[PDB]
Image (tube, coloured by chain):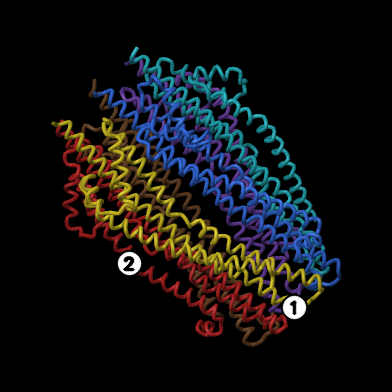
Chain colours: A purple, B brown, C red, D yellow, E blue, F cyan
Amino acid sequence: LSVWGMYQHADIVVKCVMIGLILASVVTWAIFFSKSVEFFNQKRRLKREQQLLAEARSLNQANDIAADFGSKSLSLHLLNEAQNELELSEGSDDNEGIKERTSFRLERRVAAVGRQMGRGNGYLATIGAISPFVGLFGTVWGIMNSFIGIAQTQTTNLAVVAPGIAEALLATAIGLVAAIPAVVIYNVFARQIGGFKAMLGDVAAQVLLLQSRDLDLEASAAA
Amino acid sequence: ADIVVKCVMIGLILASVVTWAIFFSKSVEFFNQKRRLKREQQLLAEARSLNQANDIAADFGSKSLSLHLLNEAQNELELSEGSDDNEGIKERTSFRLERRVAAVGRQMGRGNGYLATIGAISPFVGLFGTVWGIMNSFIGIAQTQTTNLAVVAPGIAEALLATAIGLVAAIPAVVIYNVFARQIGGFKAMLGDVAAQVLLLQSRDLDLEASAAAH
Amino acid sequence: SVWGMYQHADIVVKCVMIGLILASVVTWAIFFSKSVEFFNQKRRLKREQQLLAEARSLNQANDIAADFGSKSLSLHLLNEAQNELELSEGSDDNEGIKERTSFRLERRVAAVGRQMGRGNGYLATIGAISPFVGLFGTVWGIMNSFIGIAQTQTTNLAVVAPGIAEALLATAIGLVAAIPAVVIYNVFARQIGGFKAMLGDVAAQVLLLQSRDLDLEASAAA
Amino acid sequence: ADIVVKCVMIGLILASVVTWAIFFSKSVEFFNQKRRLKREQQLLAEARSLNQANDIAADFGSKSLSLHLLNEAQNELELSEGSDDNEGIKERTSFRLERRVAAVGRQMGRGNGYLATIGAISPFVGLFGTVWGIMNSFIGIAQTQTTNLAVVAPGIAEALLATAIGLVAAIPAVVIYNVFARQIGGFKAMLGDVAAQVLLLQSRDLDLEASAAAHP
Amino acid sequence: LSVWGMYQHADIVVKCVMIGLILASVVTWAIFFSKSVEFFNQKRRLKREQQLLAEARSLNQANDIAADFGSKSLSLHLLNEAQNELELSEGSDDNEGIKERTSFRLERRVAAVGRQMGRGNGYLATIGAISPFVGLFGTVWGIMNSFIGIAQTQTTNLAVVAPGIAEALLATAIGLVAAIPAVVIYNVFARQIGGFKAMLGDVAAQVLLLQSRDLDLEASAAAHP
Amino acid sequence: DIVVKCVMIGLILASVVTWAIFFSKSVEFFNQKRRLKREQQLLAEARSLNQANDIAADFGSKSLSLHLLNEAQNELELSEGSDDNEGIKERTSFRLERRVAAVGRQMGRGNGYLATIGAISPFVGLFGTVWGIMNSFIGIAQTQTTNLAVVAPGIAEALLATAIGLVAAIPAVVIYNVFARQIGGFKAMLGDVAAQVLLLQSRDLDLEASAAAHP
């Protein structure tokens, strides 16, 4: 017997748990292949940018390195945040206020990127968490049909009870196929987002160190 | 057939009706308030001063959240008119904005409590119906001195149906609760970023004003 | 009937049943008394918060709150701020007054939250142990089905039925006692948290008025 | 009879005796300490200065917790006699009082470790006796080649009794552990509020003293 | 009938589950007896040291009390940390920097001691975590052999399935004997390490209070006669 | 069965991945651990940051203690000409703590696979069992058998898939826990070395500032 052969011999209820769980599995692997390529390219880009910006000895030197990073560059967004804060604060005597406002902006920015990074993880979490609930529904539906079988035939043996038990076991099998990959993929991506946020945080830390040092050397020259 | 099992089933159907009713009313409330705030955040991002932010937000509407946060900062500056302590103004403004963002989040969640309880207890009220059903089938066996399972099979199948309905009421309530909980958290974070911009504009304005007075 | 079931059951299952029904009576008694208590308190604080939102100084806030009642929570927080200013009369450190007032108000709001919680401890224990006393009844019930087999020397559906029906009854009563207690405990825990947040917002307003007043007074001297 | 199973039931009965023994001793000490601290907190709430608080707390016992906290603040002021840094006195006092409140909370917890273990393992030692009992009934069936369940029903019923006793030992230990854990938490909060009052009085007194010296 | 008698009648697979779980239980109780005595002696020493150092009115007085505490005394290590900080900082005008550097050193030291106390708990955690899996494996294997029994012997009755069921139950019983004590002992030690860290933290707090007060009184004597 | 055969192959390939991480992390910890204890011991008798750089001169280019000292020296070099000593101390501690965190992250590489293999291997085993027993019941339905003996070899074979699943999971769980403990202990030691680099720099700056105030 084939999986399409099993589908045909199952009742309308278990046919729907099958359709719904296979569609849940198709969406799990579709999210997986699109997000895996998205993270790979983005980590490769940020790792190169982090290495190049590590050579900067001033915020101005960092802006020169990042000049040809691209409009959609994350390191260039963080540097533009620090430059916009110095431009708007042009004419202020409080250097500590510039540093505090820049760190506030960069940390909120890094958080916002982390939120964008997981637009599909919500689907992976729900699929992994509810797939066993629907498998259990098919399990109870399955055994209920075994008892309907006993009532209808007024007989209690393996053969009368087998169609309902096989149907119950099918719902558990499909439930495990949908749930296990969604749980694994959700956790791998949640770990990758956390590791990416930490790397982007190290780049924003460098933008902050360069700005803080530059302001201190300027304040020393005024004193 | 059983009055207790009948009550479990009508209770679960009512739980499902309430789940979808909460879903349709809250979905329209979120979609509108989440889209409006994203537009307001984009427009206010262009502001170079708190006065410029008030000009952008002039035509935002009376029920605008961004306009409430800007009015909080303006009320603080008006009441503090005549104070030498600029940090005292900044601290009082951040305290006010923090507390309002929190208060809005508390209001955004109203209706999520019902979804959580429906999703969590529905399988157990379902289980109660089947335990009760099978209990009565076994009271029946004792009373009649029955030996044949075929005589109790209709009662057992009917009892197991209560667990199936329980799981059908629970699954949508769990999914809908999690979608909304994620949306509320993401909205609180966005409203948090708008309040942060109101604070940055006020803090920078006070510093530039103090620098102009010193020289 | 439920009384008919009670009569046919063991002395052990009869005790588990009466203990769980009494646990359910206490759950709903706590529920009706605390629901009215929280509603009236939330209703009173929302009105007080709206009226005190109009205050432009701590003195104005004291005038608005004058007729709030002896048992008013907003009036207690305003009296905390006033007692701090009175005891600190003659101090040059305004920041010390602000710090001591915020320390007092936050500890006060915490203490009120603890006072709201009285009764929830019973709801938590009922909701948490009811499934375990239900499990005991199940184990006891199945044990009696095996005693039945030993006594009659026969394995049969009829022989084990009294033990199985008893076992199922203990699980049913356990679920009736546990489910409401768990729900009601969580509703109240959320309501206490929401009320503490509300009382915190009123304590925040008392602090803003005192902080602003001290700053404007210091500016007038300079 | 079964030795391993009889050992599990005597072990569970002894576990029940120790949960009620811990319960009666602890209930007596806790009630006595909570009752005393509530009275002390009410009396010390009237104090307008640290000196006034020491006068109110004179009529308190040697084993009084409120008097220990007040003695901590006074020992800090005595040892710091001759220091210009008032902020250093305040910081050292708050450090001492918070560590003291934490240490008292830890002392209150003595015995609760036993109420946690009994309530957590009792269902599992119960389960072990059941598994062991049923295992031996099946060893018996294998060795004698029986097919009648009636022959092993007394052994199976005896084995399931070990899970029932397990649950009877666990339920009171779990409840009593949670009531005491809640009481310790509520007591720590109250002792914290008394230490907070000792700190407010000392902080205010130092500030008013510094203000009186600035304006002679 | 006896535990060795059951071992002999069981499968080579059930024999392996049994020996692996019994060895896991031997190591659980061996760790338990060695750590319980080394923990008792250390807490007894620190409680005496805490009582004696509570009498100190200056950091110099604390060093005199702790002079004869012993080479591996924990209270003496904390006092040596404070003294080494004052010696290395000799010639510094920033007293706040001395206080900050000393608290940094003492908190890192208290953390390092807590990590040393934790030696062996890693084994208790792994035994608690893997024992239910190896017990489950024996149960699955046992029930599998009951089905092999139904297939091999033409018949399906209590006697045919009894050897497989008895084996399955044995694996669950041993699994519970290995797992439950390892989980309990791991949690008792984790609570005891936490309580010890808190007591050692109270001793380090006293070292810090004495140093902070001493520096403040010294600075006050330099400012005003 | 082809489905049950695939879970065995999957479970074998899962054991291959377990041996891979077992071998990479074995070599990375034997070679990087004990070296740190030696470096920390030598750095402990330092007195000055300059003295620490002399001790660490012959530590090796790939030394972690030498990387932390180079971080403190690069901060002093880039900050040459700054009056704010507190800003140098703050920037150095920020750099070192982010560096220690980054090393901890690099050390965890592979443990994610050990955790998932150990946690998920019993479930792919369970799937094979459920699938096997399902086909035995399809067989009973198709033939109308009433004898458990004809369907016992298939059930015993299906239960074998859970046994193999547990045999694959147990080594991954053990190895994951040993490595998790080793990483944590190493992070703690590297943290203590970075703490020493910070204490030396902080003390040096304070003694330098005191020498300038009263020459």
* Label annotation for residue C36: 2
Query: Which quarter shows the C terminus of chain F?
Result: top left
Residue F181 in sight: yes
Check the image and name the residue furthest to the bottom.
Answer: B144
**Position of B172 relative to B69 (above/below):** below
Residue drawn 66% across the image and 59% down it: A18
Query: Which quarter shows the N terminus of chain F?
Result: bottom right
Q: Which residue occupies the foreground of this view, B97 or E205?
A: E205
**Position of B67 relative to F161 (above/below):** above
**Position of C119 relative to C108 (above/below):** below
Q: Are marks 1 and 2 in contact (CB under 8 Å)?
A: no
Residue drawn 50% across the image and 52% down it: B179
In the rendering, at what x and y percent does residue D58 appear?
25, 51
Q: Amino acid at mark 2?
A: Val
Residue drawn 28% across the image and 38% down it: D77
In the rendering, at what x and y percent does residue C45 appear?
27, 57
Q: Amino acid at mark 1?
A: Val
What chain is tagged by disc 2?
C
Tell me the element at label 1: helix
**Is residue A40 rendered to the left or right of residue E89?**
right
Residue holding disc 1 = D151
